[PDB]
Image (spheres, helix red, strand yellow):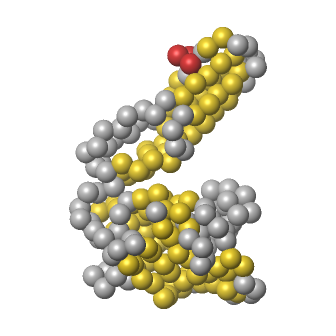
Amino acid sequence: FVTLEREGDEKIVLEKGQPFVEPGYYAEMNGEDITESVQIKGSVDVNTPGIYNLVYAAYNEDGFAKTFTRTVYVADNTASPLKSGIYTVAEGSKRTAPSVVAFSGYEIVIFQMEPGIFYISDFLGGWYDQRAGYGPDYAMVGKFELNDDNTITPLESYVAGWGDSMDQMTNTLLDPATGTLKWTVAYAGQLSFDIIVKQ
């Protein structure tokens, strides 16, 4: 009866300073328009790089509600060959242990926290949420530092729900034209992935 539609992207990347213009939404209950009834938890601070979660709610008759979430990421406008950042996993992207399995165009977010340092939604390409639908408690959040030599040095990394980090990361490269990031990450004991991300 209640209906709740999000307009615009679930995930958005702004650059520090750039205003956040609300993409909008729509809500209807029993055929009447109840869009002005929707309430939002959350704010976006476009002058402080970071991750801001908004949560939109549409209320119904007996405690019930429908909800959608939108996440806004603020970058750091400092020049860097790595742009920020809704990357799509590319097509030469594969598992390489124990078997070999190629995967598609799942999207991840990559934004600059401070001049050298970047945040990723998922080191693991979307293999475990998304292409398994395990959900956001899977996939490897992480920071990494972009080097002057177009490699990538990983700092923290973590898969909630299992509690561990990556075992190692090698074979990385950024191409400052085609603007394409790639890495091999080895995970849980015996597991390794070769990821390529474009936009």
Front-lying residue, 120 or 178: 178
Quadrant of image for the N terminus? top right
Q: Give residue 178's position: percent from left, percent from top.
A: 40, 72
Furthest residue in direction top, as rendered: 32
Q: Is residue 127 above or below residue 22?
A: below
Examine the rendering and report whether any part of residue 160 can be seen: no
Horizontal side, residue 69 vs residue 111: left or right: right
Among all residues in the image, which is located at the extreme front? 178
Above or below, comparing residue 33 to residue 197 in the picture: above
Residue 3 drawn at (x, y percent) = 69, 25
Q: Residue at x 56, y 76 (%)?
A: 195
Q: Is 186 above or below relative to 144? A: below
> Measuring 54% from the left and 83% from the top, which residue is drawn there?
184
Expressed as whole percent of the image width and height from the top left, the position of residue 145 reads 36, 74
**Count of marks overlaid on the render:** 0
Q: In this view, does 181 lie to the left or right of 57?
A: left
Q: Position of residue 149 (x, y in %)?
A: 31, 85
Placement of 36 over or under 88, stated as above or below: above
